[PDB]
Image (cartoon, coloured by chain):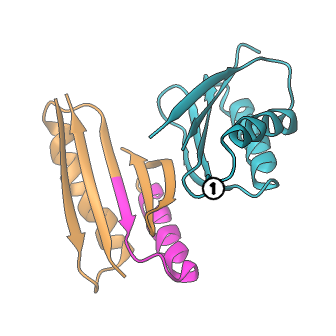
Chain colours: A cyan, B orange
């Protein structure tokens, strides 16, 4: 293991949370959208979900984790607008 | 279709953005950035990054094909894609020299 997942919600307001290890990509995505629904009503295009997989190695394992998170968030309406694999981590950006 | 290519070198941090004329192949674009990066490699510059930007992203069929053409042109010359971003009606690609 030794691979952390970090999610930051931006809507100017920014909320970053370290994901506890053990959950699945669907459980992580469901928990994040529930936190975003705490600031409900107004908040869709302005909402930016950024996920970070630390560290970025092994690249094959970290890319699979990023792909699974991409599957969960895009099945929930969000769209992957950015992906960067530099800086000892993989950084994803989702928007509604 | 507007294309911008940026070249960034670090030691502290420098960058230079140029605009590509409409009548240019993806080969001449990549060969031109290689020549600008080879001179910086001869000098004392470490991390070399290349960013490509396709400003009109209205037709994703030709915007991605322009991006996919430039991607293969830089990868066939030793550059590694490290970032893809589609925001602000533009498509940004960042490479590592």
Q: Residue at x 52, y 82 (%)?
A: B62
Q: Residue at x 15, y 46 (%)?
A: B39
Q: Residue at x 41, y 77 (%)?
A: B56
- Residue B57 sits inside the magenta stretch: yes
Query: What predominant SS class does the magenta segment belong to?
Result: helix
Q: Secondary structure at mark 1?
A: loop
Q: x%, y% of residue A24? A: 86, 31
B41 in relation to B29, above or below: above
A15 in relation to A1, above or below: below
Q: The N terminus of chain A lies in which quarter of the figure? A: top right
What residue would you read off at disc 1?
A44
* Residue A51 visible (yes or no): yes
- Residue B74 sits inside the magenta stretch: yes
Q: Nearer the viewer, residue B78 or A8?
A: A8
Q: x%, y% of residue B60? A: 56, 78
Q: Nearer the viewer, residue B3 or A7?
A: A7
Q: Residue at x 51, y 54 (%)?
A: B84
Circle 1 residues within 10 Å: few <14, some 14–19, many ≥20? some
Q: Is residue A32 left or right of residue B23?
A: right
The furthest residue to the left: B43
Q: Nearer the viewer, residue A7 or B2?
A: A7
The furthest residue to the bottom: B23
* Residue B78 visible (yes or no): no
The image quarter containing residue A2 is: top right
Q: x%, y% of residue B11? A: 19, 27
Magenta stretch, residue numbers: B51-76
User: Mark 1 belongs to which subunit?
Assistant: A
Q: The C terminus of chain A lies in which quarter of the figure? A: bottom right
């Amino acid at each position: 293991s030794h691979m952390n997942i970090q999610v930051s919600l931006q809507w100017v307001f920014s909320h970053t949370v370290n994901i506890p290890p053990g959950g699945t990509a669907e459980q992580i995505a469901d928990n994040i959208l529930d936190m975003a629904r705490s600031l409900q009503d107004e908040g869709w295009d302005k909402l930016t979900v950024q996920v970070t997989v630390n560290p970025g190695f092994p690249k094959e394992t970290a890319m699979r984790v990023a792909a699974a998170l991409k599957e969960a968030f895009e099945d929930r309406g969000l769209r992957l607008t950015s992906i960067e694999t530099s800086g000892n981590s993989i950084h994803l950006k989702f928007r509604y």
